[PDB]
């Protein structure tokens, strides 16, 4: 009851973008949305993103499997976000703001 179907994903390795997010995470259930954080001017990846699953059960399973998955010298971090999370709103925050709000912990 207390969690959304949305995950925050970070410590992405070089070359790991929206297509790789989809490829790795769609294996756990159908996806409603995949977003990679990018500098709005240069287009450069900020090396984290947000995904939403159609079934929030699947978000829990993806988080359990992909959190601390070691890929290309990176330990992927995955967090299921509490109820009320909305990618449309969270995607707008500066990275340091997500960190201050405790969303990335
Ligand atoms: Cl970081
Ligand atoms: Cl990095
Ligand atoms: Cl690393
Ligand atoms: Cl972390």
Image: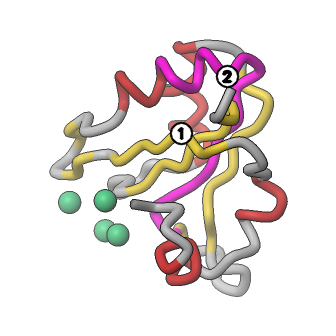
Q: Residue at x 76, y 53 (%)?
A: 87
From the viewer's perspective, is residue 62 above or below residue 92?
above
Q: Does 10 sit left or right of 2 as displayed? A: left
Reading the image, the residue beneath label 2 is 56
Residue 54 on the magenta segment: yes
Q: Nearer the viewer, residue 12 or 54?
A: 54
From the viewer's perspective, is residue 56 above or below residue 88?
above
Q: Quadrant of ligand 3?
A: bottom left
Quadrant where the C terminus sits is: bottom left
Q: Which image quadrant is residue 43 in? A: bottom right
| Protein image colouring | secondary structure
Q: Does 81 sit left or right of 91 as displayed? A: left
Ligand 4 within 8 Å, label 1 CB: no
Q: CA distance from mark 1 to mark 2?
A: 9 Å
Q: Position of residue 63 (x, y in %)?
A: 44, 30
Q: Position of residue 9 (x, y in %)?
A: 48, 48
Q: Nearer the viewer, residue 43 or 89?
A: 89
What is the crowding at mark 2: few (fewer than 14 residues within 10 Å), some, or many (at least 20)?
Answer: some
**Label 1 residue SS:** strand
Q: Nearer the viewer, residue 72 or 89?
A: 89
Q: Residue at x 38, y 53 (%)?
A: 12
Reading the image, the residue beneath label 1 is 80
Quadrant where the N terminus sits is: top right
Q: Position of residue 24 (x, y in %)?
A: 48, 27
Q: Residue at x 37, y 25 (%)?
A: 64
Magenta residues, as a range? 46-61
Q: Residue at x 50, y 59 (%)?
A: 48
**Label 2 residue SS:** helix
What is the crowding at mark 1: few (fewer than 14 residues within 10 Å), some, or many (at least 20)?
Answer: many
Q: Earlier in the sequence, mark 1 or mark 2?
A: 2
Is mark 1 in CB contact (under 8 Å) with mark 2? yes
Residue 89 on the magenta segment: no
């Amino acid at each position: 009851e207390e969690y959304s179907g949305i995950i925050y994903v970070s410590r992405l390795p070089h070359g790991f973008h929206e297509k790789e997010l989809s490829k790795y995470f769609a294996q756990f259930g159908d996806l409603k949305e995949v977003r990679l954080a990018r500098n709005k001017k240069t287009g450069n990846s900020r090396h984290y993103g947000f995904l939403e699953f159609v079934n929030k059960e699947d978000a829990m399973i993806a988080q359990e499997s992909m959190n601390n998955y070691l890929l290309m010298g990176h330990l992927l971090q995955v967090r299921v976000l509490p109820k009320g999370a909305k990618i449309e709103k969270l995607y707008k925050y500066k990275k340091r703001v997500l960190v201050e709000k405790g969303i990335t912990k």
